[PDB]
Amino acid sequence: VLSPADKTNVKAAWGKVGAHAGEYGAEALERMFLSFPTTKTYFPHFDLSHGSAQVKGHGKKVADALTNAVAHVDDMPNALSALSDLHAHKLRVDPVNFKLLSHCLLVTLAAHLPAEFTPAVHASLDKFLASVSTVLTSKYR
Amino acid sequence: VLSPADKTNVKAAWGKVGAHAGEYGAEALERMFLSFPTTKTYFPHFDLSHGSAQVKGHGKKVADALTNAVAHVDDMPNALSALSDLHAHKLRVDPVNFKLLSHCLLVTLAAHLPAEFTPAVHASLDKFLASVSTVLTSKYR
Amino acid sequence: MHLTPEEKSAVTALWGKVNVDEVGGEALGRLLVVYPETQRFFESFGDLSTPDAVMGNPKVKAHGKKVLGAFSDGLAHLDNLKGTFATLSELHCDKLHVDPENFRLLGNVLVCVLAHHFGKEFTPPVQAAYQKVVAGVANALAHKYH
Amino acid sequence: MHLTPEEKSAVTALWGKVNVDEVGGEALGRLLVVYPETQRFFESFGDLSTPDAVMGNPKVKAHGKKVLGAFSDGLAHLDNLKGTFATLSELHCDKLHVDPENFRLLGNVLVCVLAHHFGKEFTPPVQAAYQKVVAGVANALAHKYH
Ligand code: HEM
Ligand code: HEM
Ligand code: ZNH
Ligand code: ZNH
Image 1: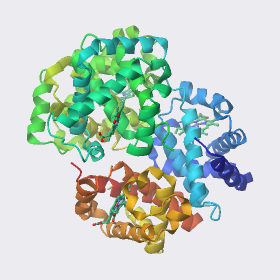
Image 2: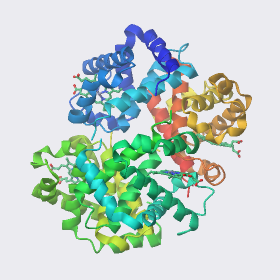
Image 3: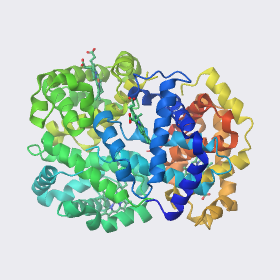
Image 4: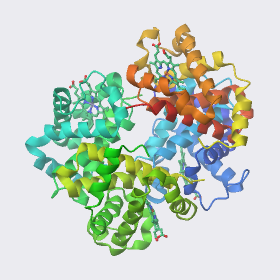
């Protein structure tokens, strides 16, 4: 469960990401494809070379979804309802992969947010991605 | 999520279990300790030898908490309120370990109730225990 | 494969009494039913709507046999699982696109299946032994993922 | 431990610029703040209630150093982690009773910290190596568990 502090922490941290979100999402994704090769089995139709337009593209898409969750941090289940249905009925991604991507977002944000990636935030960000993950994974069976 | 058919499959399967509950609980526990040794680190105060008083009584407790969960299948978070506070604030068992008990229960059941372990019941049983796991870890952070 | 001699033996002996045709079918079968997400990979097998269809589905059964058949060969190569499943691996990764996370699911479904057919004879010690093969077999299959 | 010359180079190359005393402190303290449950093993470190209490705790820092200390000894023996960490494994198992699962939490946090300290320099390719490395150590610390 996110606490009042946790939320403030996510909004402040996310706010600083600002117009770079898209740029970050892609990197998050590329760090993922590299460190955890298995995750690629979900993207056989994707061109996975460094600097790929589909990766930049999906990158933005992931960052927009996340941005929207921060926008509706008090009602995420209904905010992401759409995305949840997608991943549970069409994509059918195994839950562990969500932890991998989450971990990769953390590295990515920590590589660009020196001053803001404080312990307290790292803890709040880690909980939020866990929430986003649990929602997207909620209707699996 | 538990559908009405699952709830019914669970109530039946567990009904047949009857007075062998604790005996199955202890068995699952044993199966777990032998098959997935890392899980022993949570019971360093227990005599872990074959069929010993501690594993037995403990298996009886686990079994009975399950009985109570079936009987309250429609209200698990409230009926398990306490066990959830306990595993979350005091025992602090890493979630992974919960799947290992469930699979072990499943094996135990499957080995003792041949006629009932149908593919439909196996399934429901799996979704059942998976839910009892979330409820027991829902207050981790 | 850190299999104890008395473990290797526990494994081997029990396998020899296995009906490959029934066990294979019930394994693959139960996987699709218990973990529907895995159906994504078999949409070409046909009617996977209901438990009864799946377990009765001939294409399901036949593959269960082919699958348990490859398992058998690993039980005979326990010392070099990696080398025995290298092909099957490049194949499940380079052409089939299966998240190796699913292997484990099949592994546990299988363990249930044995416990289901052998009851008493599937004792805790024997299960542990199998739990080890199932993992060993899963890693070998994921071994060449890139 | 499938580590290529280029990966190992990166790994070692980067580690050369790391202040073990400092990085360790951050790493263990963050593990104690990002995954509170892990405090269960350090009730004798005193104040762990709020972040500053953790990050600032002089025992948390002293211990951090210790851990990261042995972690370097591993990089100097990437070819035999299981041997290097054998006694340490029996320890975390027999005496401390630490669920090996926790070894990966620390690892991933470690990765996060390196990222914080090096920014851009920590390129995707460099992180994949460390992911391999940290996993390696975790598996090695878990090997003597029984
Ligand atoms: C226990 C570990 C497994 C083993 C040893 C195994 C082995 C095999 C074998 C031998 C084949 C036949 C290849 C051929 O005939 O050319 C095959 C095909 C296949 N396997 Fe696996 N398998 C395992 C688990 C899985 C699971 C978990 C999945 C996904 C749920 C999967 C997905 C597939 C698919 C989609 C095919 C192609 C079948 C076809 O349409 O012809 N396998 N597998
Ligand atoms: C790179 C991963 C890790 C390494 C290399 C490592 C290594 C060590 C070392 C060298 C010691 C001191 C040895 C001694 O006292 O004789 C130690 C102690 C200890 N370790 Fe680890 N450790 C790691 C991760 C963890 C994790 C994640 C935990 C718990 C979640 C943990 C739990 C403990 C505890 C409770 C002690 C005793 C501390 C005391 O009271 O002095 N270790 N560990
Ligand atoms: C947080 C975390 C996350 C998030 C937020 C997300 C989100 C998302 C989004 C927004 C999208 C878009 C779609 C449309 O079109 O609309 C997607 C999709 C998606 N997705 Zn997911 N995801 C995720 C994770 C994930 C993972 C883990 C995976 C596996 C690996 C995935 C896989 C996916 C896929 C495959 C897709 C599809 C795309 C294409 O195909 O194009 N994913 N996704
Ligand atoms: C199904 C699922 C489940 C359930 C229902 C349960 C339940 C339970 C119960 C009932 C109890 C009793 C408490 C009192 O006192 O009252 C317990 C305890 C308990 N628990 Zn838990 N669990 C479980 C799982 C588990 C896991 C998995 C683990 C890990 C391995 C555990 C660990 C535990 C511990 C450690 C304890 C305590 C111990 C003693 O006795 O001290 N657990 N638990």
